[PDB]
Image (cartoon, chains in turn orange, blue):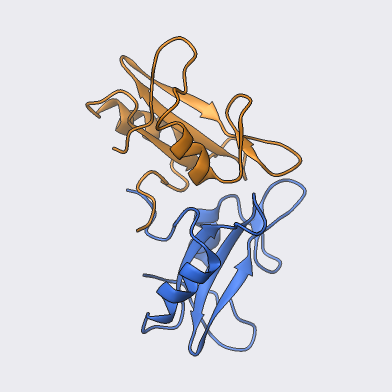
Length: 96
Length: 96
């Protein structure tokens, strides 16, 4: 089916308002960045706050958050369903 | 909500199997290319066949099919719901 986590072009502020209403930590979405056109941002509910990560790219075209590289957004998301997006607390991506 | 047209990483063959069953020209989806990691592919039903368009990116990261550039996939998609993706026929993007 289409990806439940891909929200297209929604402003950062709208993504935070929507994620802040979710019950579970790790609720998230991928949005097309409005500040850097062509870039994707991953917004994620962390307890009392919503954090935003830039989806970085390398010359090979890979996507990444820190150092492990992915051939697609879909692979990046799914990897983080099992490995935390945070170094200090265990936060896994969960569909809204 | 999430975009009805973003299918993440599904194979080109899967997009063809899905769209070939659609009854209307212009039924489409956007997927993450497996043969060109990091490229998006827009698959579209054209009557008889399913055509695959490469989503191109310019030096600033903007997206395009032919010449007009867009700040996100979402805007490229919406513009092609009323501007044909074909040069010889009028084929407008319609959600599956």
